[PDB]
Length: 216
Ligand SMILES: O=P(O)(O)O[C@@H]1[C@@H](OP(=O)(O)O)[C@H](OP(=O)(O)O)[C@@H](O)[C@@H](OP(=O)(O)O)[C@H]1OP(=O)(O)O
Ligand SMILES: Nc1ncnc2c1ncn2[C@@H]1O[C@H](COP(=O)(O)OP(=O)(O)O)[C@@H](O)[C@H]1O
Ligand SMILES: [Mg+2]
Image (cartoon, rainbow, N blue to C red):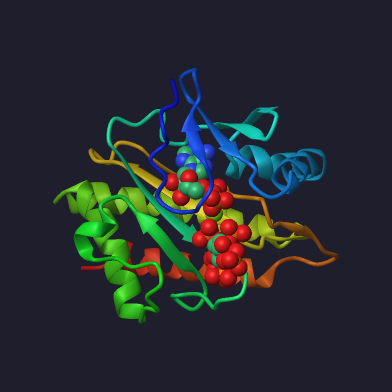
């Protein structure tokens, strides 16, 4: 019957679709996530196509979403919250890592406030599954930098407050494939300017990933 999806973070009920390449995410409190997918579809379709998993449909309170992990033999996933948290400040100042594949092995704790040193170490821990080939992990980082730098650019022209949105970083163990996408629109709001807090989150990650890519 029901196969639970292996979430990295969050609190939402998420299951595999009965069909390949789909995940079903329950909207717990309101349909606001659906309203925001549809708004972005009508007002910023290009943003939706570049950065956001496909919404294929709705079944009562379930969103049918593209499984970002589907085309991977051995996916490693990191969830980084880049939008404002509800009440708390960010564990790494401009963003909060919420989890990653194998994080329990490094005693990662999502409640722990981190220094720059510990933040960088947790991202390094996440890259460990990618093996010893410096050149291949560096190509993963550069492709993430490529898409995040375009996202930061595009966000200047989008009049949404991306409260609670996450970045889902994915790379294959063999480092042949990687991506990053924006998920979780449940608390996103209309506003009459751009979201400088969320832009600062992305530019700060671009800065951290760039030092990792340039490390000797
Ligand atoms: O601090 P946040 O905003 O990163 O964390 C929220 C938390 O989000 P998440 O960890 O499920 O993504 C849950 O909120 P929802 O995203 O589910 O609405 C927690 O329930 C929420 O606590 P609360 O809903 O009981 O206020 C966390 O917020 P808070 O710790 O800032 O209060
Ligand atoms: N489209 C997706 N494809 C693959 N994994 C996803 C997708 N959306 C969410 N996830 C997984 O589910 C987790 C929680 O997703 P999110 O939308 O942030 O839900 P919540 O509202 O519970 O925080 C993420 O950390 C990630 O592991
Ligand atoms: Mg979330």
